[PDB]
Length: 250
Image (cartoon, rainbow, N blue to C red):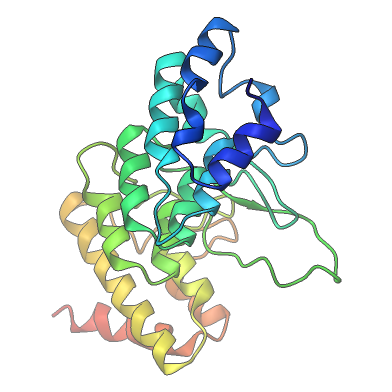
């Protein structure tokens, strides 16, 4: 006997033992971890997210097993990419939680099994009495990593051999990852320090991977390059840094 309430209890606790039988049960009953009855009616959280939120010393051994079972029984991409909503975001995915939980190990795993690397997490039109569980970060995992000051993950997302994230990708606002970086720059020392690093890290990177395309030149939907956007929004620290570079380049 398996179903939502049970299966979710089981991964919530991280018990591999309490999975024995899931594979046979699924097959013999013609059922799949992608099916609607294994999705939270409200959100869309498959058991994947559910196990990803209940890590412990940052691991949860149901994960590998679950991925495997979903591979054997059904469409594994469909599984990994299945999207969920909370009050603050819609279109969130396993990959997203992996990054917000600052967990190199499972990002690698998901990316390796076929995670959509360009999944956009979009904001919801919320209240006042709900405000503060949202922040705009680009919409994509790459932007997410960049913004939350996670170099080692940005590298992996761009340098892995399974699926590389396009640096030139623009979100729903037309914003690439540099725009994102602009968006989150406040003017604090600690902030400006990591942000410029991140910017420089990515621009230079995009130079080698694509030499005759300019990243800095991609205009968002308001028609702005990042630098323009920094000027237009009082992001002095980064605006300054950006200039100092363009020039210093001979």
